[PDB]
Amino acid sequence: KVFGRCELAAAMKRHGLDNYRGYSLGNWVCAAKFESNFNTQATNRNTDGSTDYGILQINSRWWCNDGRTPGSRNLCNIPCSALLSSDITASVNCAKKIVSDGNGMNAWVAWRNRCKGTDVQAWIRGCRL
Ligand SMILES: [Cl-]
Ligand SMILES: [Cl-]
Ligand SMILES: [Cl-]
Image (cartoon, rainbow, N blue to C red):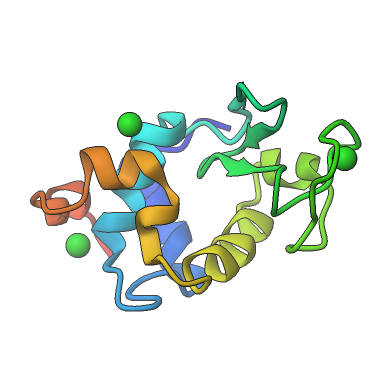
């Protein structure tokens, strides 16, 4: 599913991501924009052989099981395929664990490089939330 901008903001809020660990909704929408362009089916293969999955490009080295990432963990206790669903529940629940791991949203390199320090409120501007 490719979400609309406000549609995704609303879904993220529904699932308790808004201001989670102090990160406003615009941060999360911005991260999703640059990780996946709001496409739940997004996948990308990393140099180390791990793969990133879903709207927030969650990585199989630590967070989910794909059966093809040697030496990896599955800390969200989910198949990586769950992160591709039109229902963002699994991605949100896993993201909550990731952002609580110590480095906040810096875990998403694209958030650090493209969202951090910017006017992230622009991502939810106009949205009925
Ligand atoms: Cl915001
Ligand atoms: Cl594996
Ligand atoms: Cl980047």
